[PDB]
Every structure is written in structure tokens, then in C-alpha cells.
Image (cartoon, rainbow, N blue to C red; front, side):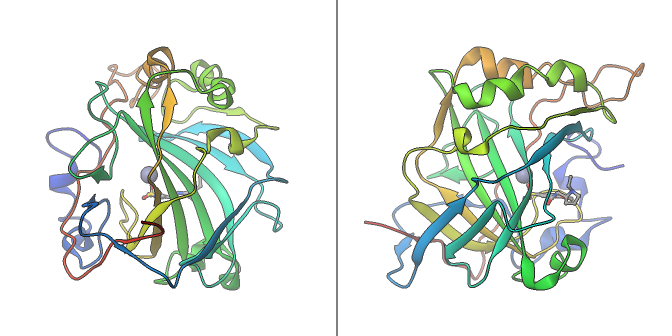
Length: 257
Ligand SMILES: CCN1CCC[C@H]1CNC(=O)c1cc(S(N)(=O)=O)ccc1OC
Ligand SMILES: [Zn+2]
């Protein structure tokens, strides 16, 4: 089965998932000098107010926090999105070290981790149908510096012991994801894919410029998680990121100067 090691890693993914060498794969490197301001972009609308988180899960790849997406209560509009995308889950990618962990790079620079808040276009009814469409999903990417602690992440960090190994899941109601947001909503956007299998090319990417600082103690607990299942050889969940991909025939736009 696919993973992040030497024998099942990203370089082995094209065999079971030929789209890996597709035309719009993610992540990519965002060259800040060639990225172009897009006057045509409508202001981004993040409305995670009546967001209802339910549980967190270790899927032997990351840890995800799930949301009731049975109403338009947490939504992402505006910017490149011509529609309304509903929040369903969010998850992280981090490294074994602070100088790596992010999936997207900025001028080749690699962050300690990267946050993916995931949304699906409501005109397609469910997520299963959404994922089969070029404009199916929109994912909000936020970078993570190691520095000062992020309070709105700690409630997450503290429940990570109860979901150490693949298959485990704990209750995670009443978490507000707005705490994970940075100050500015300035972003690069491009047409991309999922960054793990099945690597479907169904995603509009909105990667924010301004990262969040999390403490060294915080990201350290992400690293204490296991890839393996209970009572198996202990693989540490670290470096769960796919390297940047050929941009090919794509422009990374920007929402500023
Ligand atoms: C827990 C909810 N699951 C079941 C239903 C929705 C799904 C959530 N997963 C994803 O949307 C997803 C996102 C990425 S990404 N944005 O590139 O980081 C990569 C692979 C993914 O799934 C295979
Ligand atoms: Zn991701």
C-alpha cells in the first residue's frame, strides 16, 4: 500500500495512480516573482462561524478533524471560486525537522508544516461527486513557522495521544478553526490536485502568504504520532508531505502587490 517511505513513497505512486505524472498535480513551488496579481479576483470569504467539528482521526497518513457538512455553516466563497464550497475536514503535513514538512514551497523555501482546510462545491451535492469534477473542491493552504505557540491549535495537540496509531479516532466537538487562521488573507491560487492518492485533479488551491507560528513543543507532538496500527512496528508519522511538482501549463496568480 502507498505511503511516504523509500519503497512506497511519492516516487512509487505513478504505478497505481498514473495521474501522478498528470497535467495539474500538487503541490507545486510558488515563485513569488513570476506569480502575477490578478485584478479579477473577488475578495475571499472565509465563514467558519457556525462550523461544527465532530471527531479527529489518524488514517495512517495524517490526522484529520472532521466536520458536520450537512448544512452551509462553514463556507468558503469569493477569490477564484465561482460558487460556494462547504468545509468538511482539515489535516496537517509536517516534517521530522523544522526546515521541512510543508508540501508547497515559496521560492523553494520549505516550512515546518502545512495546514489543509478542505471544502467541496455544493452544486455537486456530495463530496464523492465533487471529487470527480475539475472545480470540485477548494483547499485552503496555510504555512506553519516554528516560533510562538498558536493557542487555537493546542486543543488539537492535546487530544493527539488518544489517536496515536492508524485507525484510532476521538471525539472533537466544539473546536473553532478560525484560531488556525493567520491575520492576512493574501493568497496565491492555481488549479491543482489532491496531494495524496487518488491524486484527483479536482482542486482549486488557495495558499495564504502569511504563515502561522506554532511552538516547537506543538509541532513536536505531531511527530509523536504513528503511521502504523496498534501493536505493529512503530513507524513515526513524520515527513508526510509530497514534494513539489511540475507546474507545466499553469500560472500561480496572486491577490495583491
Ligand atoms: C475524512 C474525510 N474524507 C472522506 C471524505 C472527504 C475526505 C477528506 N480528504 C481529502 O479531501 C483529501 C485531501 C487531500 S489534500 N487537499 O491534497 O491534502 C488529499 C487526499 C484526500 O483524500 C484522499
Ligand atoms: Zn493535505
